Image (tube, rainbow over all chains, first blue to last red; front, side, top):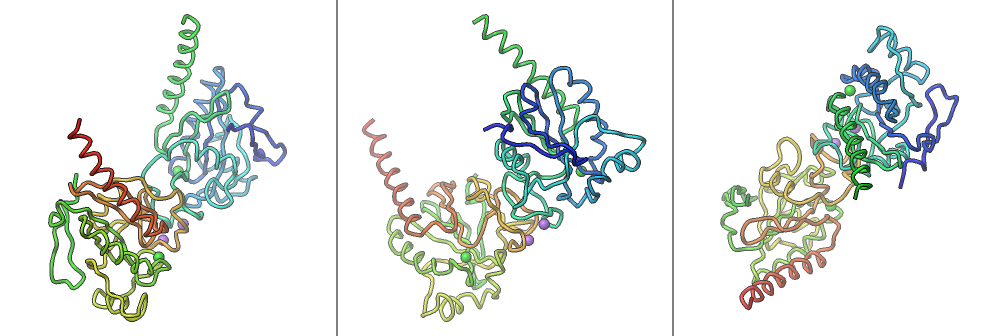
Amino acid sequence: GTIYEYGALTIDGEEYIPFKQYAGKYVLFVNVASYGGLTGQYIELNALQEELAPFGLVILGFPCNQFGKQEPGENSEILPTLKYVRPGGGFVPNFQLFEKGDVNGEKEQKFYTFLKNSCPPTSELLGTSDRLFWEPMKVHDIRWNFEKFLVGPDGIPIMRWHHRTTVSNVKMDILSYMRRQAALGVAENLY
Amino acid sequence: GTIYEYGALTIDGEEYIPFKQYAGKYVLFVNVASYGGLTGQYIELNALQEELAPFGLVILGFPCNQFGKQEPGENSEILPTLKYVRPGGGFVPNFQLFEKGDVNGEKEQKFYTFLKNSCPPTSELLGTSDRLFWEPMKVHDIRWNFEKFLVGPDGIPIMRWHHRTTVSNVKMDILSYMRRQAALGVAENLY
Ligand SMILES: [Cl-]
Ligand SMILES: [Cl-]
Ligand code: NA
Ligand code: NA
């Protein structure tokens, strides 16, 4: 029951990465889009990655066109869009992006089947179905672009955030969890 | 937090019934349709009503056109359809039917807002959205025609069944619950 059963192809199509490569690391899975209202979170995700990389955080981005069709581009067009359009201004992610694919429905990526079903969903509301480009609909489906899952260094899911939760709050929660683990380790030895 | 905050108009349009009239009774809420694959459950519901009426069971039926559009008729056409078409054969329900209305979405009947949110939903699967004629979609939505809720004699919800659970199994569960309550009453007095 770990993420190490799975892997994904990098966005340039050149390398399949088994998630076992992230053994010993905290992994933050984020489904992404280039034309979302939350696409500015890319800037904050870069900052989070740079700040917490020393403590074992790895961010992985999964482009998905299932939420308002907000990732229309081919895989080769995604990095250019981020750099020159939105966020634009020369932006380049400092974390790994993978090929575009489904996160919900019959053709969803299997590691997302695992992740989605490991934690309760992020809201009671699925939303209006016209905006949700998949079938069938299920209680634990990802609700929108930029939903987030934290997986621990043992490959086991820890927690899941609503897409609109700020990246600062996500950071604060990761740090708190890492501190609790450190403290709980020290305390177990004294005991 | 009881069903006694609500009521509904009978299918003939002649009487509004406050659910407080069912104080002291077990109430089984069933959303119904005339052209459903489960419409034959009407025959079993009649039998359940006749068998458990002496022990305080009341069945209430709420026609709804939101599931495959399987209740197209006007209110005055529903009883004739049941009697002459499906189930047909002269069938007449022996329990009260109310006016057609919504059970999910923005215009859902308020007592169903209460009921749906009182118990977990009946399956992980909502289904394919083309068959579900409401918006927005929510985790606790009724899944199909013939979902069922039991409310106790104090007006508080007890349990909820999947639509495909057989009426014999529903009966067995009601009876078991009523027996447990009787036994738990006797046992509390001895104690
Ligand atoms: Cl977005
Ligand atoms: Cl049905
Ligand atoms: Na849809
Ligand atoms: Na629909």
